[PDB]
Length: 54
Length: 54
Image 1: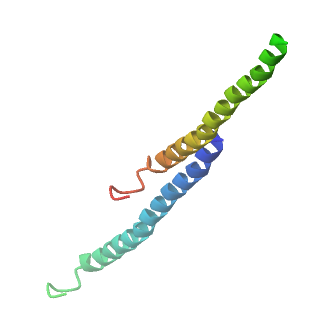
Image 2 (image 1 turned 120 degrees about the vertical axis):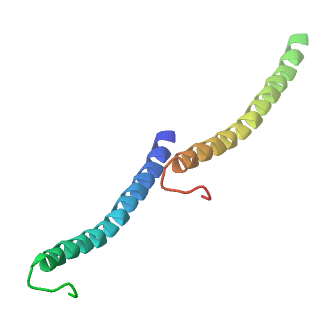
Image 3 (image 1 turned 135 degrees about the vertical axis):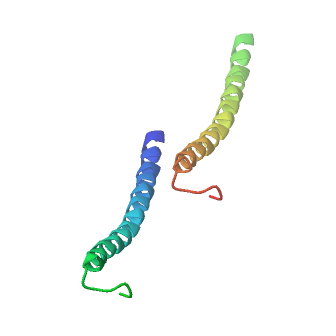
């Protein structure tokens, strides 16, 4: 009975861990997409055609 | 006759001993009922998921 109840809260605890992991993974994509945008536009700026104002 | 009456109060005697045995047992099941509740929520609070306020 102790083990059965302990497992009942154990799956709850791992559900909390899986929820925290995916919520950090949600902010993971927002960061990765922003980083990709900087890299893409850095190549755009690296071209010598545009002037300093651009 | 002495033995017969002595046994008669002896059945009453051991029945009283039985009665206090079950009264203690009645508080026994409730005592372990709280202890199981303590242990289960201690498992719940052992995660890093909850903060200090929880």
